[PDB]
Image 1 (cartoon, each protein chain N blue to C red):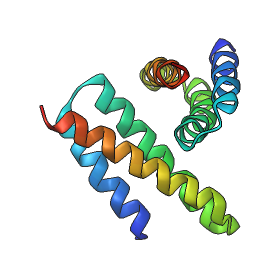
Image 2: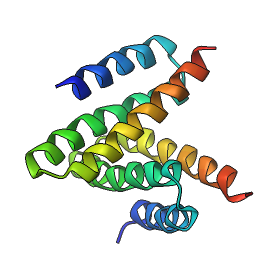
Image 3: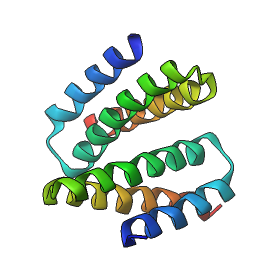
Length: 67
Length: 69
């Protein structure tokens, strides 16, 4: 799904930064990938939406670090 | 209950008090950290435990930042 792919793009961006804050974001993103698969299998749209918002905020953080 | 989970649960209560989507995002991250840390402990992965301890530290700093509002 698009979630996993966007999250993996974000993971590659975090990997390029090579700092503890970027490692923390990378780990959170791996966890979100697994969480989002579980929520989809669960049929939990609320948790899916929560994880989409997490992805948006993690990406904004990555952007800031990339500045 | 382990000391990591206790630290994460206190941070989860503070995030619930903040009641904004950023705080809800942090709350969700902390729940996932608790489960990740239990798994890392079972595996004896000291490095992953340290990464998760740092994640908890950074999440708490974000929560602190919000709480001065």
